[PDB]
Each structure stands twice: as C-alpha cells, then as structure tokens.
Amino acid sequence: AVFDLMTSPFTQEEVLIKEIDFLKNKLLDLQSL
Amino acid sequence: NQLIPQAYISNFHNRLTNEDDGIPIFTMGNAVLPDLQDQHHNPFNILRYPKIRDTFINGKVVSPYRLSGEAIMIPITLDIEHMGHTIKDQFLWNYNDDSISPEEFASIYCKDLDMTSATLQTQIANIIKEQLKDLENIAATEIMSDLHVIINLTCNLQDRFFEDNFQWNLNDKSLTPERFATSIVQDLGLTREFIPLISQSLHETILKIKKDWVDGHLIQDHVPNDAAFGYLSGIRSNWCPRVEIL
Amino acid sequence: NVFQSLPKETARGVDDLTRMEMALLSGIPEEIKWSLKKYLTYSNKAPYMISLRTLPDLLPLFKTF
Amino acid sequence: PLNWVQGPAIFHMLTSPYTQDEIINHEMNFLKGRLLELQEIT
Image (cartoon, rainbow over all chains, first blue to last red):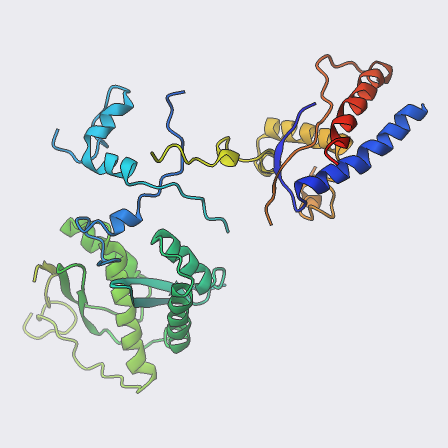
C-alpha cells in the first residue's frame, strides 16, 4: 500500500481506469483460485 | 527544519535593472559578500549584507527551464530596444552547430530577463537568422600566404573603452583569440566580463580581414607597421593595450 | 515572503521514475540494484506504467545488462 | 507532456516470506482494500 509521485502521459483518472482494468482481472484471477 | 531550500530564488532581473550593478543588458568587515568570512553557522548573519537580503526580499520563485567537425564562430550582435529599456550584448555563434535553435535561445534569453513577451523571441531570432545567413560563408575562409596584418581593436563596455594594437597572423591558428583575450585580462587585472567581449570583438575583426580577402580579394600584405625589432629589419613594437576611461 | 510560494510537487527533489532512470544511467551499482528492484516491483504490480509503448527509451537500458 | 499524477498503491508487505501461500490472503484483502476505495471514485 505504497503510493508514488511520477510523470505520465495519462491523467489521474486514466491511471485509475488502468487500475480498474488491472485490479478487476487480478480480482477475478484470485477469487477463482 | 530550519533549512533553506536549494532552489526557488531567481532575483536576477531585479539586479539586471538595479542601476548600480554595471550590467549593459538593460538600461531602464568591509566586504559586500561573505565569500571570505565565516558566520559561525547562524544563517541570520547573512542578512547583515545588503546585496543578500536584497535577494531575500525582492526575490522571486522560479520554475526550472527544461530542454560537426569544425566550429564556425560568428559573433552575433543583438540590439533591440523594448519598452524604454534596450537589449545590448554580443555573443559568438557556432554556425556549424545547430543543436539549439535561435528561437530556443531567444526563449531562453527572455526568461532570464523576465520578459517572456513571445515577440522578442521572434525579433531576437529573426536578427540572429539574419546575421547567421549574412555571414554564413564569410567566416568559413581558408586564408594562407601569411597576411600578417596589424590590428587595432576597440571594446565598448560602460564607458571603459579598451584599446590595443598588435600584429596578428591570420594564417597560423595556434593562438585562439579567446585565449588572446584571456591573456590581456589576466595581466591587466580586469573582470571576467572582458573575456567574452574582447574575443567577440576580435572574431568580428577577423571576419572583416577575412571579408577583404574573399569579397574584394585585396591582398595588401605590404609592410605591417613595426618598430624595427622583429620581422622587418628597419634599423635593428607597435603599441600596448590600455583600458581608456572616456 | 519568497519562501512560502514553494511548489509542493517539486519540494522533495526529483520524482521516483527519474530517480530510478538516472540510477541505471549512473554507474552506481547499488542505485542500479535499487532501481532494478523498483523496476521489478513495478513490473509485477503495474505493467501499464513501464510499458515499452509508453516508455520507448527503456529497451536499451535493460539490454546493457 | 507532463502530468504529475499519484502512483498506484503497490502491495508492499512488511514481513517478506518466500512461499506464495502466505501472500494471497493479505493480497486478496489488499484487492478488497484497494478496489473498494477505487469504486467510490467512479
């Protein structure tokens, strides 16, 4: 649970959207097993 | 705590327009600085110096600006009047180098002036693109045959006009004119601002003797004037430099 | 009065992505050790951040190892 | 183009074992602990 400050070509919500796309797959991967 | 940050002070445009610091850019104990005196590790002792709390009170906070086989040195003059105050300086330009655009330099230059007017950046670079294109093949000469000319040189810096006379051979490239500019300032005891200005006013003098060799092709290598001691045996030098306060 | 308008996003130095990038770029092997440990942590936890499509000049920095 | 954005929450656990089965229970609570705080932003 460590955050960071960094530069990105994406804004904050698209990183949160990319966090939505990454965590939901990991949620489906871990709950299935 | 109790620590000064490493950045966020750029009180330079106020010293550009301070009218006591001898800056020719803009017009409109007993030490001054403790660079030889300790302060016993209390930072309040640096506020006793008048040119330092001037930078703490009148200072600002900046954001940091973020960004070939033989160099062709072309001295570029920049003379632009801009709302009462002017812009007057001189700088060489590596014509063979194109790593920085003149518009990129002019946006760099008007940031330290704290102008950033975005039409100075056009007008500075348009003069630079003028003077590079006017001199693009006049500083790339190949002079041989021992021209050995005499050179009178003048340098203008805030009514402190420097003047010298010497015989220059623009056939051997052993002596850099910047190195020749440094040997005068080392021996005369002048400030560091005469290191660029003597060299920048000599490259323009060089490309003028280069000019008469390539434009009109006047050789005129006929007795560079001496005092009968060295090259031409008359009876068996010319002058010595000086900084004249007019 | 000039020490209150400090930008808060750059009052800590440089950011961590450049701090890892300059670490491999320097010859400091423990900073190379630290940044490679951070790069493998960020590879397992957030591959969208250090994707080669996002960062094109990341591929030769790993090829020299 | 610069965008000073906050980095993602990386699950860095204090005690560091080497077998995987002692990580998944804290990581599943991390996925519950991170996606539920991320769902309310939407």
